[PDB]
Image (cartoon, rainbow, N blue to C red):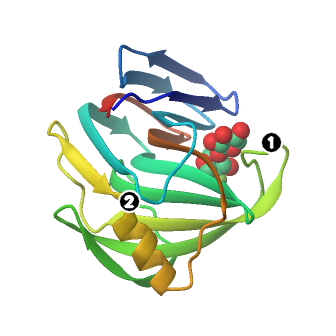
Amino acid sequence: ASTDYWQNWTDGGGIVNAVNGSGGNYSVNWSNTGNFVVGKGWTTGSPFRTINYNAGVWAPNGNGYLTLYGWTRSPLIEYYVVDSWGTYRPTGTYKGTVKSDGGTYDIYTTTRYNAPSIDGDRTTFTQYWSVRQSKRPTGSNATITFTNHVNAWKSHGMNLGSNWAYQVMATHGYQSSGSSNVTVW
Ligand SMILES: *[C@H]1OC[C@@H](O[C@@H]2OC[C@@H](O)[C@H](O)[C@H]2O)[C@H](O)[C@H]1F
């Protein structure tokens, strides 16, 4: 499907060269960054969405995640389905596991303090995570059946807000360098 949304945010640290490519294709080259997130996907997230992607290039040198990435409001929640990463596997408060799309993912919560959110400025908000137990190989057509994650999260008291914001397959980085090329559909 057409992705109707382009996410390209940087806190301004270092270099984030983000290319909005043809169709659902994008690429990022980044160097010595602060926080950034770049992705393609949908203006309005859905708990029923099934995301296809193929990361033609997945080459982080440092902390970068290849991840479904989205927000809700009411309440304000930042959520992730992490399929691969760089030198740092994201973790937090272990809640359980979920099997989806051929992988086993650990379910985590964490909380961010005084940090930017989709509202801009700085707040405290909750983060919900499914994180693959080992890196998904890249270069093939992969699927993230998101309802499997939403249902598993609910079973652990992790309920998303009712106001859906954007929902993208992203490259998410913090204080690192790398290159990625991802097609989303
Ligand atoms: C989740 O990832 C990075 C950052 O998210 C951004 O916040 C600012 C907003 O305008 C963008 O749309 C977000 O991607 C957040 O602090 C972090 F915890």
Q: Earlier in the sequence, mark 1 or mark 2?
A: 1
**Cβ at disc 1 under 8 Å from ligand 1:** yes
Q: Position of residue 167 (x, y in %)?
A: 51, 45
Residue 36 to residue 100: above or below: above
Q: Residue at x 53, y 49 (%)?
A: 45
Say which of 35 and 23 sits in front: 23
Residue 140 to residue 90: above or below: above
Q: Position of residue 152 (x, y in %)?
A: 40, 78
Amino acid of disc 2: Phe
**Cβ at disc 2 under 8 Å from ligand 1:** no
Residue 76 to residue 98: above or below: above
Q: Residues within 10 Å of mark 1 (few under 14, many from 20)?
A: few
> Nearer the viewer's eye, disc 1 or disc 2?
2
In the rendered image, the residue lying farthest to the right is 121
Residue at which label 1 appears: 120
Position of 43 compared to 179: left or right? Answer: right
Say which of 46 and 126 sits in front: 46
Say which of 181 and 52 sits in front: 52
**Quarter that holds the N terminus:** top left
Q: Residues within 10 Å of mark 2 (few under 14, many from 20)?
A: some
Amino acid of disc 1: Gly
Q: Position of residue 122 (x, y in %)?
A: 83, 51
Residue at which label 2 appears: 146
Can you tell me which quadrant of the image ligand 1 is in?
A: top right
Position of 146 compared to 159: left or right? Answer: left
* Distance Cα–Cα, label 1 vs label 2: 26 Å
Q: Residue at x 38, y 65 (%)?
A: 147
Position of 84 compared to 128: left or right? Answer: left
- Label 2 secondary element: helix
